[PDB]
Image (cartoon, rainbow, N blue to C red; front, top):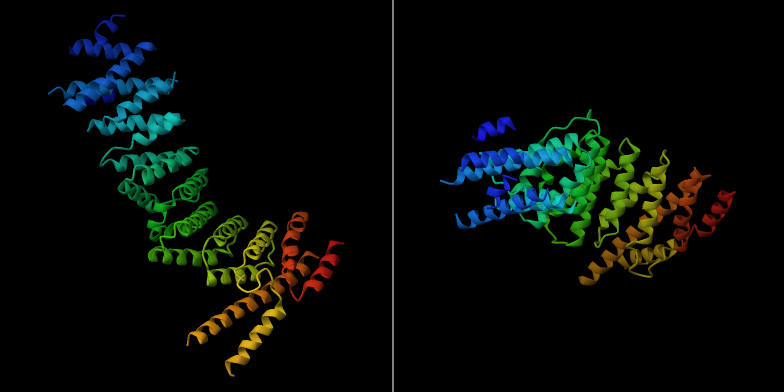
Length: 424
């Protein structure tokens, strides 16, 4: 009577610890040391009959009634024992679909180490990806704190258990499901979940980036912030274990182009989050010649903004790009305009007057990049000097230009004079 039991959803110790009617009476009576001894004896008996292999309907019944009574007891509420028993009965691997559903949904309603193990070991179902996907959807739609837990579970599915089929399936369903902007507390939870999944397991979130394009054009600012932090963490990871993959290279290219596009988005929060993302991905272990060049140009054209926090975030951008500038090949920590101009003029005079030609032309391109960077820093210093003359922007911008002046420039004395004129 599996369907009937699903729809409906002392003297006993003398027979449980030592027929159908007796089993039904015991199940009705059981529906706390006796409960613990019963769960251990049932767990080891199930493990034994599964390791040793007509009699399956009795076990099916017993497990159905026991799961129902355990669900009732847990939704009614000495706790670690029942979690341990659940983990034990989960290792022994239709009615199983409803069984795992009635284990997951009440636990989702109730929702740490044993609970984490329970949530990790209950996804061993095969072919039932639709049910777990639907439960995760209802969790993300109704629950808020379960976002980081689902992120950790997907991470364990990524690296711990190494089951890429379920991970790819869940990622495809997440990237293909429709989203609405009128959701209350929904986009924030989804953004937190995606941020945690990116900072904790960015290896799978990158493979399906060809489909997250529809999520890249989301109207919600929280989703845009989340995907920006996600691609930032992805670029960081791809700089850690370079793997030097070509598909990952073109993914980096397209996401960084989207970042240059979003650098002028119509919201201060998404702009600051993109600023944090490029601040996290600029100081990695790579060259990024054109990447840093376009970073510097788009930071020098947008330094004269209108908001407050975006201005200080761009100042921190300039600070981080100055303290880690690639112009350290010849006489590093020195950006004298005349020192580069004289070398450029000498190279241009030597041009009109094979490997040697390659090396001198690459040095010429390097000097051109250096002089463009120095004219950009000059114009940005001019802009910030005519703009500064909010106390937070005043107190956060001093450390930037003092180290900018530490690198000797032709505007050193004029910059100091402007600083003095500004401080009063």
